[PDB]
Amino acid sequence: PSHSGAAIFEKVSGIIAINEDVSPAELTWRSTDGDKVHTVVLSTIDKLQATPASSEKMMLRLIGKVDESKKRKDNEGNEVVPKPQRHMFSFNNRTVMDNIKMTLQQIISRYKDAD
Picture 1 (cartoon, rainbow, N blue to C red):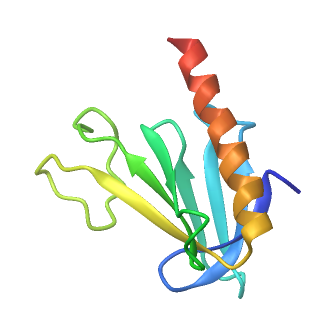
Picture 2 (picture 1 turned 30 degrees about the vertical axis):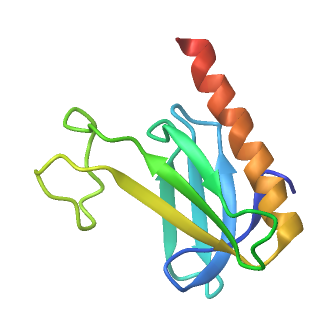
């Protein structure tokens, strides 16, 4: 279960799954309740940031590039004004965050192959 692991998003915890069967791939997030499901685009991730090993708080932040006038906006608080969107996640498990972090990094490398 390296591609899928529990992760928090917006003070809410749920299971995070990595969907690569599509194109571009996407990271799915299902709440613990299973009533709310969030999907993230891995193609719009210029990079992947994570908390240091010296921080008891496990959180992985993803940079949603800067310019996205051509890319469809999430519509969830995004305005016409071009601005960089970042998604900060909170992990309740070091091993779980490490399983996703390393897995998410692989996807990046895959995007580089394209160009």
